[PDB]
Length: 188
Image (tube, rainbow, N blue to C red):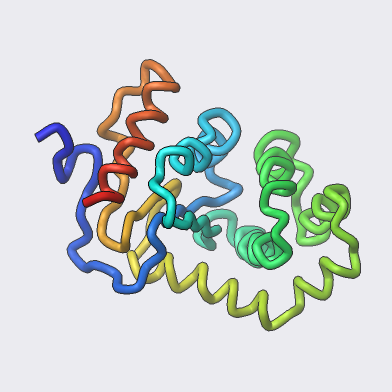
């Protein structure tokens, strides 16, 4: 066909019930993830092609960057709880990969302060049990698909995007292929 298992996507040997409809994993240590976010705006372009009635979920992972990697997963839980994903994503990426000024939880915290979240509101979120279970959700979702690599997108707990199988001579064309693939899988 035009879309084929093993080409634009793969199928899970082990489907995951009750999964979010469009589920994306990343790491602020992940170089392709930086590309995906700041250069290609994948999440965004997928969204604008998804039918609506469809929610999009993005989770951080632990397996890159050891101790900081986990701090970053908890901080992304904070960002989700406060609804400030859109104000910290870029400075977290650049602070980890561009300027390399993020080396500790305290530096992660600085990004949120600079983004305007109050220290008080941040420390309370950081320490809240609502953030604990949010961390647990991120870990569980990654666990359910035995996630060993990022960036990664899963559709309806049963399909995994396979970006390796798309032309990259043009960035715009890659993005649209990627998004259309998501929409195809979405309708499947």
